[PDB]
Amino acid sequence: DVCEAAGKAIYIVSDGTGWTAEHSVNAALGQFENCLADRGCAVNTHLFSLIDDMDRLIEVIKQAAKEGALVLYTLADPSMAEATKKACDFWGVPCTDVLRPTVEAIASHIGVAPSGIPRSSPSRNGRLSEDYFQRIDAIDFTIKQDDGALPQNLYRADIVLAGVSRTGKTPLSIYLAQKGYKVANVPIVMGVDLPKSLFEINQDKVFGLTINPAIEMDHVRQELVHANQIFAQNPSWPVIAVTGKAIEETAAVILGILHDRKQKCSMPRISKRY
Amino acid sequence: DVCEAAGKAIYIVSDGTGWTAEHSVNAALGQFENCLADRGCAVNTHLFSLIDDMDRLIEVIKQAAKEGALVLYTLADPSMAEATKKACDFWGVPCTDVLRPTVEAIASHIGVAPSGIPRSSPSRNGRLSEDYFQRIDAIDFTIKQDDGALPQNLYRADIVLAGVSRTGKTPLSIYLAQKGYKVANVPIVMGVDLPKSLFEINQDKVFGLTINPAIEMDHVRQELVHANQIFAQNPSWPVIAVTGKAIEETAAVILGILHDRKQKCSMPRISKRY
Ligand SMILES: Nc1ncnc2c1ncn2[C@@H]1O[C@H](COP(=O)(O)O)[C@@H](O)[C@H]1O
Ligand SMILES: Nc1ncnc2c1ncn2[C@@H]1O[C@H](COP(=O)(O)O)[C@@H](O)[C@H]1O
Ligand SMILES: [Mg+2]
Ligand SMILES: [Mg+2]
């Protein structure tokens, strides 16, 4: 009577949350879209957060071996990394440290040795940045948002999404809010007037969103027509075709454009100070 | 008259969005918490999305060299990766491919060669998964949430956060919603009764959240006392101390516990089928 044979397995193992790795794995898996599409292959990801000591580490790998699984991992303490590869070797199981390469490149380039301490440990912790606390007020602003008090928000908002219902306004607005931006959504509906404040605010920062209907319900054709006229009336608004694109993709388009305008450069790019 | 000398620079460069890399960089930077704390060092991240051709690639590195900056990158096409390292060598600039290691480990372990095609290109695209469309309904459920229609939601919700105001309920609920979980928030206030449906729903899935006040306003002491009594009355609820912890940390705690119960195992872990 058990829960864990079926498919090729992958262990994601971190002394912290496991998310950085899960992200990298998620992206990596993209290279086998077509494999996974038709179940040509199939994968199981198993995520082990908070692996901050030796005993617990050794058990995971033991298990990984028992299950027959690749171990992708992230461990701040160098000894733990050594141990992981040694114990992977000893149990005869494939492995790979997904971000020491990245940690070390940064370490030489900055010219400082890594602390070797995870986020988990008692030292330096509770040290949440100003970047983080900004993203909270963004998140707050963006969800705490009725259409009753829209005008005022359009002035405050860093980004303004404008588009018909079936564009991804809510997820996207939330995604951008997490990145640090106060976002305001303005739906385009046949037969309701847009707030005049939409056009009085800074017109850089309004972004049109649109669906390609090519992917009865030709009312949607009607709406998309009406929408494009609004967008014509407003040439300076970028108009992003949104269907079959991930939020995170669209978000990058918007942010590239936003940052390119917000700071005019030789080479256009999204920049952050640390 | 220009925008881009000050601090050590880092270029994040992807044929797609740049996010996977930015994530890995963000995490990596953790190893130099104390360096960056006192401005012992200081860093600039520059994010270049959609670098899907040679000319544009070569310009970025040229710029990177001009700026004197490390290039961390993600490129599906092998030629582009070669080109990147060669041109980095030619301009004499440090670099490192942050996820081919991970792509290749997966490729041997699964026993299939990577497609070498980015998300950007015309082939296979618009192929958004069922995992993704689930996360949308989650996101929808979690924000589209008044306290008027709370009971009903507690039954539907996959996770239920219960805690006083100053716990991170809204950000966290949103973060979890993006991961796939319908979340319901229940605030604990002195002098308002909790919905009786809180106690009639599956009691695995309620998670208490609490602030350590150690980090006039001893009303907060009053609230935290009252809260803990509710939590005492309900022993099966985990009670996560939340202050000075990131959302993503807390989220992992909750999800570990959730998954551990949801599927009882020898080794506790968060699992996903692909
Ligand atoms: N602020 C931080 N301080 C120290 N290490 C960190 C920090 N943020 C992320 N990390 C490390 O980066 C890796 C990323 O994994 P995770 O945090 O689980 O997504 C782990 O080994 C963490 O310990
Ligand atoms: N579904 C996918 N198909 C192909 N490549 C992907 C997919 N998802 C992510 N990637 C690749 O993974 C890397 C991650 O970068 P990013 O997508 O910008 O965060 C890029 O080189 C992308 O092209
Ligand atoms: Mg991780
Ligand atoms: Mg990337």
Image (spheres, coloured by chain):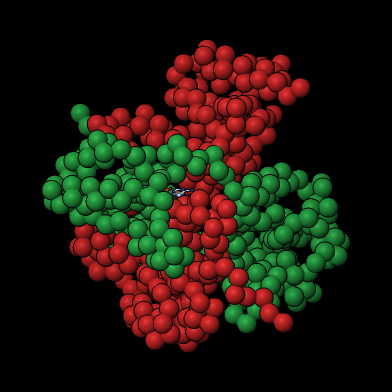
Chain colours: A red, B green
In this picture, is A225 found above or below A137?
A: above
Q: Give residue B124's position: percent from left, percent from top.
A: 50, 42
Q: Give residue B188's position: percent from left, percent from top.
A: 73, 60
Q: Is residue A124 left or right of residue B195?
A: left
- Using the image as rendered, state which of residue B118 and residue A100 is in the foreground: B118
Q: On the image, which quarter does residue B158 sit in?
A: bottom right
- Using the image as rendered, state which of residue B130 and residue A145 is in the foreground: B130
Figure label count: 0
Quadrant of the drawing holding the N terminus of chain A: bottom right
- Residue A133 in view: no
Instruction: Residue at 26% x, 60% y: name it.
Output: A106
- Using the image as rendered, state which of residue B170 and residue B49 is in the foreground: B49
Instruction: Residue at 86% x, 65% y: name it.
Output: B200
Instruction: Residue at 60% x, 19% y: name it.
Output: A227
In this picture, is A168 found above or below A216?
A: below
Q: On the image, which quarter does residue B273 sit in?
A: bottom right
Q: Give residue A247's position: percent from left, percent from top.
A: 53, 41
Q: On the image, which quarter does residue B63 sit in?
A: top left
- Residue B144 in view: yes
Instruction: Residue at 46% x, 39% y: name it.
Output: B123
Q: Is residue B258 left or right of residue B119?
A: right
Q: Give residue B157's position: percent from left, percent from top.
A: 74, 56
